[PDB]
Image (tube, coloured by chain):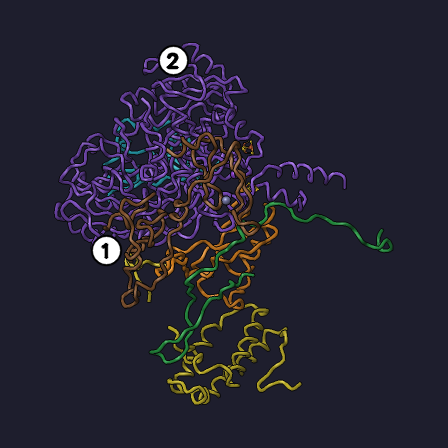
Amino acid sequence: PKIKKAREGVTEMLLENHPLDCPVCDQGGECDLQEQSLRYGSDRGKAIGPLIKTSMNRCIHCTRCVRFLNDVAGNSELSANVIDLCPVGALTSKPYAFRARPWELKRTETIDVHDALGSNVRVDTRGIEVMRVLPRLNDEINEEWISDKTRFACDGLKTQRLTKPLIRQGNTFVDATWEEALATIAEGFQKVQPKENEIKAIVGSLTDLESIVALKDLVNKLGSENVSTDGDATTVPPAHGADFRSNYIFNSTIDNIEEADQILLVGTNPRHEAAVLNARIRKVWLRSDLEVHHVGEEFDSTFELNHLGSDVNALAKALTGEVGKKLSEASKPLIIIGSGVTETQDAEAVYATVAKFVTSNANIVTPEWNGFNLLHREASRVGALDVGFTTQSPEVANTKAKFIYLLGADEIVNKDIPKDAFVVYQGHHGDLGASFADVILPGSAYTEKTATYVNTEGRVQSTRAATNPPGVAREDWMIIRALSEYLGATLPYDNLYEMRSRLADVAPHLLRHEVVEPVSEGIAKVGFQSLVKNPIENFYFTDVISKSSPTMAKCV
Amino acid sequence: TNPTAFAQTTRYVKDSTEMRTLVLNLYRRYLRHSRGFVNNYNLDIPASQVRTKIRQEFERQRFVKDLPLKNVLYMKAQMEFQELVNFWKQQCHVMQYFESIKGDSFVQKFLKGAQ
Amino acid sequence: KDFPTTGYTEVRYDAEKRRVVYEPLELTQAWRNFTVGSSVWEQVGDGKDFTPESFKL
Amino acid sequence: TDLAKELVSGAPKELITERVARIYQETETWKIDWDILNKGNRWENDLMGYQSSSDYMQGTILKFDTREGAIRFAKGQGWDYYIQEPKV
Amino acid sequence: SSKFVFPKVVKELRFFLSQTGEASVPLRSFLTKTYPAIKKANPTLPILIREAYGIPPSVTARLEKGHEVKTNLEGFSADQIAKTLQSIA
Amino acid sequence: STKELTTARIKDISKPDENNLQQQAPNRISPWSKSQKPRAEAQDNVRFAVKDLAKQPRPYAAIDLIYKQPIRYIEHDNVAVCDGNGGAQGHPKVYINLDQNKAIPCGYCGLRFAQAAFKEDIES
Ligand code: SF4
Ligand code: SF4
Ligand SMILES: [K+]
Ligand SMILES: [Zn+2]
């Protein structure tokens, strides 16, 4: 009819100066110019970064590369989202350029592990190699946005990988079988004969929860309790404590941020600590009457703050002055504590000061709202706390342990590892934590395993396997049970379901996939009764995969 | 058109008891041809061995319950009888039919690669 | 539809057995699946009716 | 649903037990595919770099129409499965 | 007090209950009020609370050498819960 | 010398030899792609034991036959048109904007272009 000419008009106009670059387009097989110049149209007729392969020759304009920048992201931690927004191949990804075609890539739906958000992503693989990671829509967490760290650390899994067991003979690791590796640990285990507190276990940021739970059973049957993550919590028991869920979870969850009034930043840099949520605050900060006050080390943000200072004593006058008066006035006030609090010297002062303001008012904690939340940055801390994988005595943390078994742990420079101790590292990369090792057991990349992860909001999100582990690597926990038989501490778990069967005894929420079990208003207030410098140096050197990623070498 | 040797019409039996008697005669038919299967296919196993394997075949799946799935199992077993008695399967397939076939601990499977 | 296009087993010759034997499937090159980049949009609509008017309400 | 149809489909014994089928939704219909093998799903051939495989269900996808229709099929064949609810 | 400070065998305490419903009414009450008594006196005994949607009340503690004995607390009163937890050791 | 043969480079420090059967190509030693397997490594296989290396296919490397070709120049215009330089049996026609001040290669042929003014500047 007459209407169809409109499609035949706009289609003709767009394909006027357009380059004939379809064979050489990076995303030539999925641009919404071809697929929309076929169904509706007729038939006849500078650079911005080491991340985005700009070619405005292929633009159709619409300034979506412009409208997004001044709205969501605003030297930008989120500028890579422009790649997924431009329909035509005007702005294509540089690292992925000229490597794959969409009709060949296999897609899997999984989650990020770089930060504690655990945003839903879609991974496009090719055989035994991951090509690109794209975000999959989820309004509850991310909603189409992932930081440049997540989507450009993919190639970090193609180098530095541990593919074989390694054994130290002198000062250089050698290629040794699994039979000897699982014995050299047990052989040297009884050479030094560690005592009850002479065995230590450190869990890394990327270590999954199945290994975290399954390691305790192996540790317990050998009688040890020097187990915790690779943080630097001055208080040996966690200041929030693993006792109650509400002590360390985003009781609001992500879907309860856009309806807030007052937000408190307890020593944090949300731009560098959670990019997805940082823009979420910026999106609200534009139209709403949002008020956010800065309490912590000074930094640079996409948005101004009601900045106060840099010291803890700045917060002393906050909850009692007009800074905290609006918190009382807020129908849905927000308190956020970053992962950089427990590391600080005054971590204990943080919880008592704030929870006194959460045990005072009643509008903060309603049957529909909880004003206190935590913002961790690792994907293994919350999993550790929901399973009680943390110590509860400074004396145990002071022991000069003779056998430290690392499980994904890297940030252990401030951890006093005795020189004479027996250090066994199990992981999937060669980095800081690997040098300290004596017998190395290769693990699995997060895309190569079915690992049940827990984000900073308490949501239990697992992964679906994408590729087989490289070389002769095995699953993370499967080594521990394999290691169990070599020490006389065999675990009764013989398949991945039984590992989830064990999780049933740990808690009921661990077996609810994509389902968040909250803390009830009648109990979370009891958990409140228990209580009564930016942690990150380099944005592009935070996790193991980023450090080994050739792409991030262009981000420095 | 003239149907071949050892043929039966494909009929949807609507009785529980009749199917019981049809099977029993069928099992005897296999045992009657025990000597032939050895001589026809030149099997290395003697006549008693074939009956032993046939019994292991018939004992294996005697506990089925669904009548609609009883006829299907009787129909296809008839084809197996008809194919074997008419000397249709090659020699190799019968030799490998009887030549098919305890697990291992988790450490054994972990080391080599499991599945 | 649930039967795989490559089948479950394939045969070869085993010299020790001196016969051609079935064996579980093994592919040196697996069947690449290119349906993933299929159409995400609509292709064809209702069309134009041609029903003779004698067969309508 | 109660029928042991696996004795008439002729499928190998491993499909009933050792394989897991995902019922997902890519935007109006549902699909079934089998999760990848632990090892031997894809190994690089040492001759020409071909993507070898021993999994015979890698290339199989069944296009369904309705969710309950897919679940009816999985129970009919005696298949272990799990269902992935799409995000709204 | 009395027997609140559990012996050295008790190394992990887990408290599981339903956020909603009526079945977990009593278990919430016992843990809500009596928590501070054991907590301060037993500094190194973890007090694990893991909530759920409608599951019956259930409390199981972990002994030495990685052993647990399953214990149920479905439908007890607000004071008989202490009695049931006394018998573990 | 066991160093450049297994590393990808823009050019070759040494002058290549046509008669060296360990090079990636007769006209280039180091491979021209990061993922490309060096020829010296590949020939160290079981199937090259008795097979003669002289007769194996060793086509000349592409990344050299282009850089020998002198850069084309455009006079008094800033749009370069290239369609294979062979008629209707070439690559699809592409227009090259000459605003940037260096040699911008063609999409398919790899031919490089310039302007009238920057002829002295680009050649530096
Ligand atoms: S954006 Fe689409 S239409 Fe334009 S050149 Fe690339 S593939 Fe062709
Ligand atoms: S987003 Fe793409 S199509 Fe829109 S103006 Fe930018 S380059 Fe052009
Ligand atoms: K694009
Ligand atoms: Zn050209």
Q: Chain of mark 2?
A: A
Ligand 2 neighbours mark 2 (CB distance < 8 Å): no
Q: Quadrant of the N terminus of chain A?
A: top right
Which chain corresponds to the colour orange?
D
Foreground pick, D18 / F41: F41
Judge from the rendering whether residue A342 lies leftward or rightward of residue A507; answer left or right. left
Q: Quadrant of the C terminus of chain A?
A: top left
The reply to the same-chain question for discs 1 and 2 is yes
Looking at the rendered structure, the kind of residue marked 1 is: Thr
Q: Residue at x 59, y 69 (%)?
A: B68
Q: State the residue position of label 2.
A: A308
Display colour for chain B: yellow
- Residue A540 is situated, as x and y percent measured from the top left of the image, at 35, 32
Q: Residue at x 62, y 39 (%)?
A: A15
Q: Chain of mark 1?
A: A
Which chain corresponds to the colour brown?
F
Judge from the rendering whether residue A384 lies leftward or rightward of residue C46; answer left or right. left
Label 1 to label 2: alpha-carbon separation? 58 Å
Which chain corresponds to the colour cyan?
E
Q: State the residue position of label 1.
A: A177
Residue B45 vs D18, above or below: the answer is below
Display colour for chain A: purple
Check disc 2: other Cα within 10 Å, few if <14, some if 14-19, many if 20+: some
